[PDB]
Image (cartoon, rainbow over all chains, first blue to last red; front, side, top):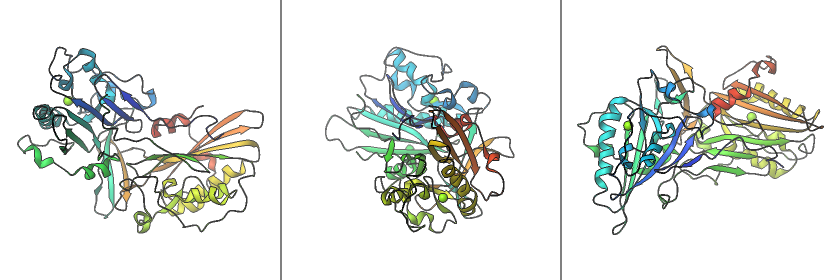
Length: 218
Length: 218
Ligand SMILES: [Mg+2]
Ligand SMILES: [Mg+2]
């Protein structure tokens, strides 16, 4: 048999209380995380200190981000499935502090501009019955003086956790009616101004689908 | 439950007559390719023109490598599963010319030193009843002027096909008496001296396992 000893590659799905993620052991962070925020269900009892992030013991130690990797890095532990999205229940929001839900994020971006869009998705849960949000990183290519195009991203910690160049957020908004409503955003991993209107970052989703390796048109 | 709209990330395993691969839609290349070389049966009468490659149709057109991506790159279409490994059957060799089995490779490496390593793998079908080979790319970080580590690789064509910085090859040498011995090689995607003994590119498998995100030890 060709599979006599096992295949080296894992399809690394995780389904937590609060989201589903697909994990990439090479980047030491998630490919995508999808949550369904419904209203009804956002605001609730439960909280946790802003810094109580935990490594994921379901990920092999070879490919597992640790708090030490972020230590001294200048990057926030930016959660993709946001914490205030799941104040519904306690470990429903404890699952959002696993480092599998986290990518190195420029702190000004984590606290102001990505934060405003997190609010926007939390505001749009108001016009539509159900709001599904899928979030993840981008590593976008970039030319230099020689004319050739390069992907270049920073790598932090001894475990070499990748710092994304960009992040995407795609929302498909509905149950209560007829169900069109797809909206796609991308911001660079950089101190982007809070003043810029949120929709200056709208992008067609195949932009994201080609770059990310994922397919969203279902 | 939130999976009501499927998942955007499909794990990608193809099984051809000659190998199992696992595909990466973001790099537009295989994460690994798994062959089982057996002492002679896989050297028969098959043959194929050396540049006759097919773009894979089992991969969505947003994430697939094409021959136009390679055309002006300066890079060889280096087959990870070697074509000479499967003279056994015409289809077993035609499978190795799928572009999903191919990564951008510096042509001097493809034809002198990587070639010697594959000729070395085919050789060791002397001593061992079975020789398993797993080949794949590596994207290794390098340290820059500012003291930070970055992963930097070129992308070619307008599907942005990742140019690996290194290549790994793992030999699982099954001796006739059941005994299995392990061997691991990493060579840079560069013109490297074919006169250097292949012994100098030996590396520990945990090193490939931490860099690639794969787990090999059976
Ligand atoms: Mg945050
Ligand atoms: Mg070759």
